[PDB]
Length: 352
Image (cartoon, rainbow, N blue to C red; front, side, top):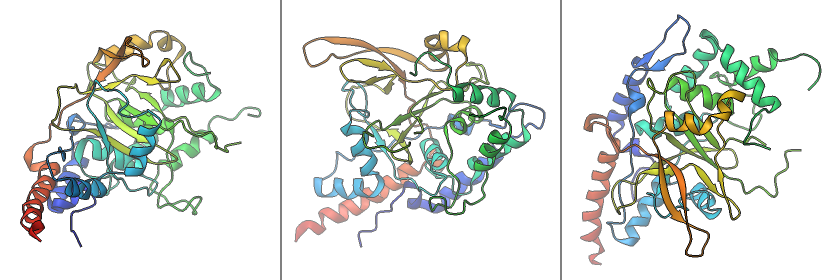
């Protein structure tokens, strides 16, 4: 059948191997005290190519193949994604939901490849085992009991319950607690991840859960690499999408329109613009959160449409990085060449 790969890395599995090979070698594994972190690959960003340049029947062939139409529809339908008309569109790439989707999602955002070799999944577990997690454990216990400014047990036990969280970060398999190859990761894991990458992660999650039955995992929000100074970190975010219980990358589109590369730092709430939740902040930081954002992100103000009445409000948005992957490690180009060719062969074919 119409052989147009389901993922961008299939267009050239050899190149994909090159990427997956350079990755672990780019990991700084300081056995001194600081967390394991990447030296340069975390600065990479990929963008999807424009398909609005192809015939409709064909444009759909592509979208059906690479995009997670389910999460796309869901997050867009609740105006949680691409609701802003002044910024570029973000697209959700399919990602394996084998319990390591957070790593596959993150890995795809910057590299085009998934965490097939469990390098990122391994970096996380290594950090939580061979590094000082005193500050992580702290921020974890804090937001657990809940202690912030933009959100809303028994008798002594915060070392074993934490212990487990470290087990989930492992490559071990659950006893089909839900039926996946790896254990599911939560908030704290995302936070440690953005520190290992020294790059902020912003998760766009589904709120539509009037039918939820969790007695909930509030993943949506901003994860800043607070264990590092904004100077030693990358000021461009990694945008992820999140629905029932699955992560997907929300990569920006490559060309069309004069709109800017930016991701609004607010939600198109019910009539109001609510600020996005910034995870694991301390009482102090929480006070200066708008400062930290301007520091760890490249914050800009954008005049967005008001609430359907000639009014316009000024909102905060983080600038999104532009595709910077060198050709020798750029899978979007190869996949593009595939579609370019099957297309010329689609025009000559549609002569029937």
